[PDB]
Length: 163
Ligand SMILES: CC(=O)N[C@H]1[C@@H](O[C@H]2[C@@H](O)[C@@H](CO)O[C@H](O)[C@@H]2O[C@@H]2O[C@@H](C)[C@@H](O)[C@@H](O)[C@@H]2O)O[C@H](CO)[C@H](O)[C@@H]1O
Image 1 (tube, rainbow, N blue to C red):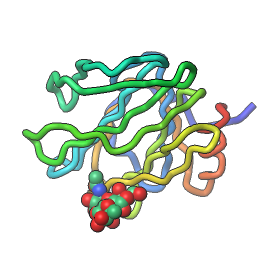
Image 2: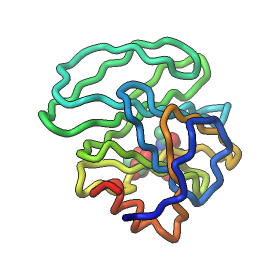
Image 3: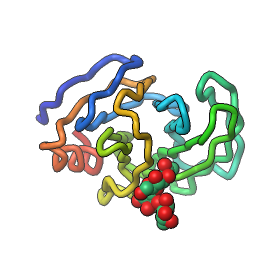
Image 4: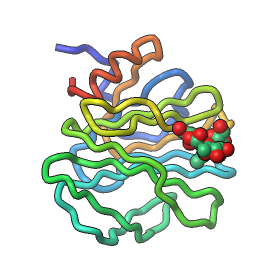
């Protein structure tokens, strides 16, 4: 089988730059979040297949918020990437990953957070947000793995085909 660095237990830590954090939730709902503490608070949530347009509650940056979500796929899971731009602001939707594999991944590099988006088996690191803070903490509700940038091809393989 594939050999990855992990699984690590859910935690909050200063994710080092140039590593994919491949997150592997077992449950729907909040999966992970992070912030530069100044102008980006980002979060991903997992939605099961066959979910009509609805409002669900998530606890993001410690606060209970209602967010509009949907997943019209009969078979694919969906990660949704939400971001708020100021401490007291509301989250907007920026990207999604529709997947048969239930894995998502992000990396801190070049002052950005890169994120795998699209639909498996053709998801790719096509989305990013700007954080300009290499010491931005991430918190995770799921087990996760770390993959060096030199193995981006493997991260892409895992996102799209599973471990
Ligand atoms: C939420 C956030 O932090 N956005 C950054 C980010 O914005 C980029 C980025 O999301 C890429 C990902 O593929 O898509 C765009 O390029 C986006 O830029 C924004 O949209 C485009 C079309 C332009 O109008 C651009 O001016 C705009 O910023 O990176 C940029 C810098 O490259 C900003 O830092 C955003 O705030």
